[PDB]
Structure formats: C-alpha cells, structure tokens
Image 1 (tube, each protein chain N blue to C red):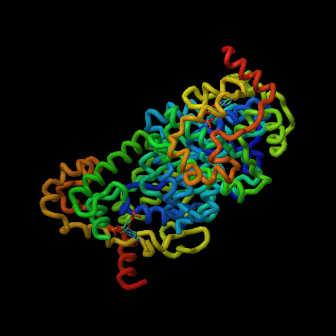
Image 2 (cartoon, chains in turn brown, yellow):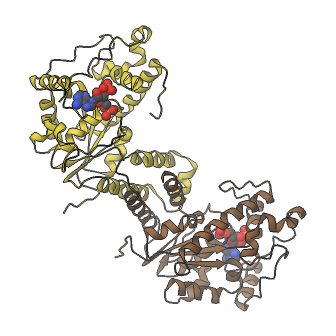
Amino acid sequence: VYRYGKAMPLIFVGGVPRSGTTLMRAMLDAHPEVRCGEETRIIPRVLAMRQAWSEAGVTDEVLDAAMQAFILEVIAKHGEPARVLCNKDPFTLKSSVYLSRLFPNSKFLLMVRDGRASVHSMITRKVTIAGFDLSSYRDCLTKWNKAIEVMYAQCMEVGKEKCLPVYYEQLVLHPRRSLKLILDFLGIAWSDAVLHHEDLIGKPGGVSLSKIERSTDQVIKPVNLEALSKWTGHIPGDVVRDMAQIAPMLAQLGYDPYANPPNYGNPDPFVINNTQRVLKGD
Amino acid sequence: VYRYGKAMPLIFVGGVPRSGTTLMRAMLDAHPEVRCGEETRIIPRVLAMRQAWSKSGREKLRLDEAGVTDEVLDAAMQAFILEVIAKHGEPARVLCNKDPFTLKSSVYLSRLFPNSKFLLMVRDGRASVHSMITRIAGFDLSSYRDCLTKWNKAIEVMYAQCMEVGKEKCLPVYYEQLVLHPRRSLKLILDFLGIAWSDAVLHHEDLIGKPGGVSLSKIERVIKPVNLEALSKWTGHIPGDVVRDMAQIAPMLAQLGYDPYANPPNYGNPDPFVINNTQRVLKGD
Ligand SMILES: Nc1ncnc2c1ncn2[C@@H]1O[C@H](COP(=O)(O)O)[C@@H](OP(=O)(O)O)[C@H]1O
Ligand SMILES: Nc1ncnc2c1ncn2[C@@H]1O[C@H](COP(=O)(O)O)[C@@H](OP(=O)(O)O)[C@H]1O
C-alpha cells in the first residue's frame, strides 16, 4: 500500500539528451525502493505550455495546484509502484526551480556529459531534438551550450542541497564511488544492485525500458567505457578551432575545450571487466 | 468544510459563444448551493492538447510504451481539471464550470466525471453570428456566410456529443425558451440536475459580487435581469443572399427546431415576469 502526495521524496533526473540520463535513471530503477521508469514526453510538454501562460480566477496558486496533481498522477501511474518515486525526462531540468517550489522535497540530478560526446552521439545516431539541427556540429554545440547553461543556472539557484551535478564520465569510470555519494545526497540507504542494473531489466521492482527510446540498446549492457571518447577525431577542424567560442560552458564545467579529448581519468577494475564482458557478447 | 473528488456532481455549461451561456451560469451561481464562476480558459486548452496526443498516431505508440496510457492521462486530466474547478472561485456544495467549447468533448468529460451533468445552450445561430459579428478559435471576422457555416459545424458536433451522452446526462437548453420562460426552464433544469429549487435563481442580478452567488470577470464580453432585448434584434441585418441560402449554410437550425425560412421564427410569448424585467432595464434600474 503506497501513498503519494505533493510532499513526498521525488527524484528528477535530467540534462541534455545523450548525457547518459537513461543510464542514470536505470541504476535507480534497479534499486528496490526506487522506480523512475521511461521518459514520459508529456511532463516536459505540459511544463512548456505552463511556462508559456505566465481575472478568470486562474491565479498562479491554481495553475501550480493543477500542475502538482497532473504530474503526480503521471509518475505515480505510468510505471510499477515503489516507496521512492523518480522521473526521467531530459528537458525537465529546465524548469527545476519551479519544480522545487511545487514539490518541496523533490531532489534533482543534472547529468553533465562532454557536449562533444553528446553532440557527436546525437549527430551520428540521428536523434532529432527541440531545435537541434543535425547538419552542423557548430549549430548543435551552440545549442547544447545554450541548453546546458540554463539547466545549470537553475540547478545553482536551486542549491547544493536539492540539486546534484552528475558527471557521466565520472560515473562510467567510478560507478561505485559515484552512486554512493548520489544516493547519499539523495539520503537513501545503500544497495549494490545499482551496479548490476543490467541484471534487472523487465524484472519487477527494477528497470522498465522503452523499446523505442534511443538510449536503450546501450543501457542493456552494464556500465561500460566504450562511449567516453569515441567522439574524438570526428569534429570538423574549424569547430575544434572555434571550440571555446562555441562552447564557453565546456570550460566552466571543467571541460578543457582544447583538450582533444581531455584526460577524464582512470577506470575501476569493475568497469574494465564489464567492458571486456561487453566485447565478448554477454 | 467542502470535499471534492472525481465522482462528485459537476455541472458543465457550454455551447457556441454568444448563446447566453453567461446568463445560464450567472443564474446558476446565484443558487446558494452552486458555484460556476468565470471562464477558466485553461481547461479547454489542456483538453485540446490531450486530444491531440491521442489524436496522434506516432506519439500514442510512444506514450503507451512509456507506461503513459489513456488511464494515466485521464487520471492526470481529472486531478488537473478538478483542482482548477475546486480552487478558481468560492467553495460550493455543487461545483460548475463554464467554458464554451468544453462541450465539444463531453463524451470524454462524462467518462472522466461519472456524475457530471451537461447543459448545452442552444441559441438560433442567426442571433449568435450577428452578436459575434457586431460586438473565437475557428471563426472569420468579415463574412456572415463563413460565421454561420462555422456556427453550424460547431453546434453539429456538440449536439451529437450531447446525444451520444444521453438525455440523462445531457440537456439541450433553449436560450429563447429560457429568456421567455425563466421560471419554467429553471424548474426543468434543477429537476434534471436533481438540485433543490431556490428562489435566488430568478433574482441573479441582485447577487453579483455577493458571497455564495455570482462572480464575474470585468473583461469577459448579464448584469441586468432576464430581458427580452437580445431575442430578435438580429433580423434585418442579414445579407439577403445569406438569407436566401439559409437552409444549405445551416441545415442544423432546421433539425434543432429553428425555421431557416422564418425571419424570425415565432419564438413564443413572454412571461409577465420577463416583460416587467425588460421594463425596469429600459428605465435604468
Ligand atoms: N551501460 C552504459 N554504459 C555507458 N554508457 C551508456 C550505458 N547505457 C547507455 N549509455 C549511454 O547513454 C548515452 C545517451 O544518453 P541518454 O541516456 O541521455 O540518451 C549514450 O551515449 P553514446 O550515444 O555516445 O554512446 C550511451 O553510450
Ligand atoms: N440578463 C440578460 N437577459 C437576456 N439576455 C442576456 C442577459 N445577459 C446576457 N444575455 C445574452 O447572452 C449573450 C452572450 O452570452 P454568452 O455568454 O453565451 O456569450 C448576449 O447576446 P447578444 O450579443 O445578441 O446580446 C446577451 O444578450
């Protein structure tokens, strides 16, 4: 018997697409106490319009009250129940300041991935997004740039207490250390299942996957390294050149725009072994 | 302490604008047990979208897969619409809402609120199209021919809806009958609603801005009691050609009980109550 209300502890995962957000949430679904389930599509959509509209008696208080209820139901109902509910829709983190006012005990994880990886990913994989023109890296990166800048600004306004930035490459390399702190920030008791998400797909309490969502056939495998840097070499020289003009965020976030790639770090044995397993066809 | 939930008894007012929907609701608000309030503008808005999503072919496939099914949607819709209706005005025992185009989706609305009732305001389209031309999403600002055809398509849908809905849930309410016979119509309506008669109903003008009664927006396009003035004023101002093609432009008038060739039809005879009301208004009360 699970209760759900305005004031419950919620988790919102997000960031720019291709930022291992599916990965992020999948490890949280695997946790027994937690469910995120797939991307809703609808929640961002109703927020987009929500943004838009801000005598009829239709005051801020009402719209918000209506939003609360609307969103609550979707998350609650769109998947299997749990004690801690979570939702993953990349662009939500756009409205996070608002979201925090609605659900004063929700928390936020903002997936930060080298946009060079993100933009490569979306370009090679043909993943059409809101305004992201697939024909120019320059376009995409500017866009990524604008995008990320905002969500971060939000996350920062929000506060260290409610929003936690989550570095995809830090995660891929050191999943064990990562999740620990994550759930700690989240304030939930440890479970090792996190690292074994791959083993909980289509299984109850665990991880529910959309077979038409794009970041699927990669999340099916365990935390693997293959993606971190396959982007390097593919960037148009002139873009590589204008790198810090097109994406000053790179720098701010600690991504050396002129490092091609940077040195992200060194892998845990766990991950290496996983990656190996991946090449073998497990 | 007023409670609220999915299944409570709701009143939906609607119909093509300039059909006296404000009157209808204004008189309802006057009831001490009832509150409709203003047009919200948002509810029909969200519905349309919800419609679209389902009215899609590719996004549904998507949405279901995500675990976001009709049920959830509906669940959300409910929760959403509810709040608005619950919060936007004064608390009441019976809650009602008025947003013209709502009644375009009553089929779905009734599925959402199994104990909701619907009043479809039906005013001769010649008096609405004139009203609207002289004083909407879908309509054209420079043709009577276009305004009517459109009134036509619009009212043709809301009625089929009201009809599939069932006499029991949906009641066509005739503007001219209401204005002519306010005590008769309101008796037949509270009845169909199963709401106890109160006398405050016929005295709506005295209860604007007053607690338990009629709340108005000062920028909606009613302040006077039930008056005869708006009934036949439309006649004479219709381009002869549109008066010639009347039955093709709106076959609906005919089936609704409006004679497309009577200019006007003979609507009926006023209550001594509505005449004395028409008289106090010409005097400046
Ligand atoms: N188990 C896993 N290990 C590492 N990366 C994963 C993963 N599952 C999914 N991903 C990554 O998820 C990224 C897309 O992120 P999102 O989840 O926001 O769409 C993909 O980036 P690439 O397309 O560069 O590989 C993919 O590599
Ligand atoms: N007290 C009253 N008596 C008669 N008709 C009224 C009224 N208050 C409002 N109405 C009518 O309701 C119509 C607008 O209603 P709605 O809310 O459906 O748009 C107007 O039509 P006209 O524009 O022809 O005058 C107006 O005459």
